[PDB]
View 1 (cartoon, rainbow over the protein chains, first blue to last red):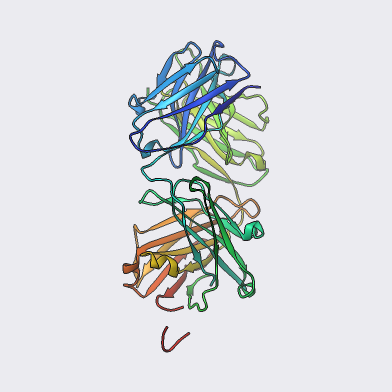
View 2 (cartoon, chains in turn blue, green):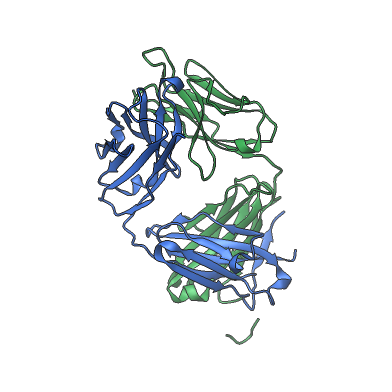
Length: 229
Length: 226
């Protein structure tokens, strides 16, 4: 019944601080040998160790954090807190807590929390603009460009979920403006373009926006093709 | 004091049933002063937290299948999977907790190997709606290819573009194990209307020669326009 449960996601402005929590169940934080590691995972930076608090309340921090982090444990709730101050975009990551499982497992991290996403940005919460990618072997591709929203995620479905086969929704990319953008595409029979309605449904809960964009054939297309094999 | 873990390879395409081997080399000794070596292996599947596989170099954590084994001599350590099953796919991390700060390897992504497949390529001009707002996004789509490596080059009136595009790639698809990729070229409306021909050229192992998709702006026909 050993478990670690972390607080929900955080979106915050640069220069601000964040306090995330880690509640342990099924065992005692004061059990000799036990401790709580904090680790973060970034998109291309892999995993990095951040800090550790031991059963005797001893605290250690990674020098790379430049003393911006503080660990507290209030032993009421069996909950450990990590506070990180003066945040910048480089602090944007998924933050995990994990139990250093004592001598028996040679202090391996045997149980992990579900992770907390921390996004550090100056962008305000904002719904996406949705633009059609008009359709153009008997197969045609069409889709929708979901542009300039914050934060993640958006959900995209086609024809209210009726169309799922051949659908690709791409990972969002952060633009230089601090806003996200993605595309969702689907391949369909070209003979269906005149008669089948194709609608992308874009949900963005953080801004409480729902958009349904019908994607229509172009009326003429002169796309050229060269080379290939 | 400051240990770098060099984990290789960064990605490992494997067939189901095959043996897989992942190596991890520390930049210096990770033998603790008490004589023990605190080397651990973790597996993180997509959408999930990392999970412990092996601790103290070679000990299997409870519930971990015996097809997983670890070994280590000096500063060289190895995770072995005797027969790869579908649930073993994901990213593997080595970790030393002997010296402070504890450090991780960069990770090894265990992927499903398959036959080469050429992408289907599509190009999309910007919508009228987007142009009204003063921005033009041109999108190049690469559908269902393998392996992951692909070259997408934007060309505008034969001029090679750089720095004004961004790519996004899907994970391996659950049914056919292929990838898909989108590339987006973004310009101001003013710059977009400065030029006639927009092209993306795709180079991939599955293609005998690079494929180009292009369009001529201001077009799709007519004599007298619009």
